[PDB]
Image (cartoon, rainbow over all chains, first blue to last red; front, side):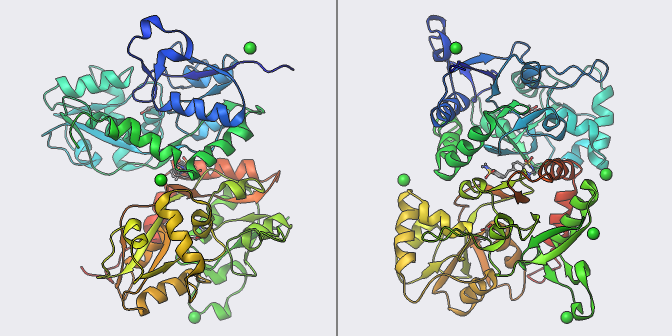
Length: 263
Length: 260
Ligand SMILES: CN1CNS(=O)(=O)c2ccc(CCc3ccc4c(c3)N(C)CNS4(=O)=O)cc21
Ligand SMILES: N[C@@H](CCC(=O)O)C(=O)O
Ligand SMILES: N[C@@H](CCC(=O)O)C(=O)O
Ligand SMILES: [Cl-]
Ligand SMILES: [Cl-]
Ligand SMILES: [Cl-]
Ligand SMILES: [Cl-]
Ligand SMILES: [Cl-]
C-alpha cells in the first residue's frame, strides 16, 4: 500500500536520545538530539522512509515476565505491533532474537564496572569477594539477564548477592545508577555497558571511571518485528554506514568531541 | 545429510594437526574454527565435513567477469553449505550470501617488524621508504580499494601501483615478508591475526596504532539456506555461555614464547 510513516521506538538514554535545549517549544522529531537521532536520520535516508521518533512509554529496554510471559520495553513495542522499528542502544541477545529481528550490530559494547573515583575495586572478582561495597545493574535489560543466567563462578556469585541484597541494588534508569555511584561515597559500584560507562566518564563532575576489562563482548542492533520487510534494507544500511566511517564519526561526535572532562 | 563446511588454513583458526598424514576427515584439523564448527553442529543437530577452500582464498568478485572466488564463491556456486572461518562480514558479501551475527570482533591493523619507525596509518601514508600491503582477495584489500577517507585512499593509490607488488597470497607470506624485510615492509592485516602472531616466536613483530575499522567475522551460508536461522541462534548461545571467549583464550593462549 501507500507509504506510511514508520513508528520508531527509542529510549531517553544519553547520549543516544536526549531532550534538546528548547524542546518545550519544539514538536515531533525536532524535540530530540543524539547518536540514535542522527542514526535514525541516516537509516531513513538510505532506506527511503519517513519516520516518527516515539519514546517507549515504560522507559524500559525489554524483558519478558517469567510468570505472564509478556514483554515490556522497546522489545514489547515491537512484539505487540506498537512500533515498526527500534533505533536505540538495544543489545542483541538470544532471547530477544527468538522474538524480534536484529540488524548486524552498529556499535560494540561489553558489561563493565563504574566506580566513584578512588573506590578500591579493580575487577568483578574484587566485587564478588567483599560486601562493604554494594553493586547492581539496570532493571529490565540485558545486563541483569546476563547475571541471572551466568554459570561462570564469579558472575553467579555476584548474581546470588545482587538478587537478595537489601535495599535493592537495581535501578530503573542509567541516570539513577550514576546518581547512586556519585552519592554513595565509594560504597556502590554500578554494572553497566562500556558505552554508557565511557560516556559518563567524560561528563561533569568527572568523578566516575570505568575499571577492569569488559565482562562480555556484544553489540547493539536495530530491531524490527519478526519477518518485517524493513529488516533487509536496514541491515545493508548499517553495514554501509560502518564501512563509510560514519558510525565511528558519530560515536566520536557524541562521546568525545562533546566531552566535559578535558581534551 | 552431511553438511559441507568450507574453511581456510589460517592459524590459529584451522591448522593441520601433528601427524595429520595418518589421520582422516575432520580429525586432520585443529583450531578455533574446528572447535567452533563442532559446537555449532552439535547445537544445530547436523553432521558435517570440513573441507579446505580449493583456491585458498577468502573471497572477492572479479570486476570484469563478476565471478566470486574463495569461500564466498564456494557458497555462491553451491560447492559448500556453510563457511566456518575468519570470514569478515561486509556489505558486498551480504548482498550475495548470508551471515550470522558475529562470533568474533576485529579491525584492520598494522604489523611492523620491531623497531620500524611507524606508529600509524598516517605515518605509512606520508613516506615511501617502508613499503606496505595487504592480503589479496580479502576484505582488507577491498577496504582500501573502496575507501574515501583521505589517509586510506592515499594508501590505496600507493599500494595498487607499487612495484614489486605489495600484495600477498596468504597471511603467512605477509608475515614472512615483514620478518625478512629488515623493517622495510609493514603488513596491513586483521587485529586477531596480528595479535596471534605477536605472541609467537621469533617474537619480532608487533601491532602499532589503533585499529582502522571495527567489524566482525560471521558464519556464512548461501542466501536463503535453511541452516541460517539455527546457526545464528547457536552463535548467540555460545557467546552468552562464555564459550566463544573460552575458545579465544585457548587458541591465543600465551605460553611465554615471547618474554615471561
Ligand atoms: C560495529 N560493527 C559494524 N557492523 S558489523 O560489521 O556487523 C560488526 C561486527 C562485529 C562487531 C564487534 C562487536 C560485536 C557485536 C555483536 C556481537 C559480537 C561482537 N559478538 C562477539 C557475539 N555476537 S553479537 O552479535 O552479540 C562490530 C560490528
Ligand atoms: N542495552 C541494554 C540496556 C542497558 C543494560 O542492561 O545495561 C539492553 O538492551 O537491555
Ligand atoms: N577476514 C578477511 C581475510 C583477511 C584480510 O583480508 O585481512 C576476509 O574475510 O576477507
Ligand atoms: Cl503515515
Ligand atoms: Cl605432522
Ligand atoms: Cl548447552
Ligand atoms: Cl560430523
Ligand atoms: Cl577524511
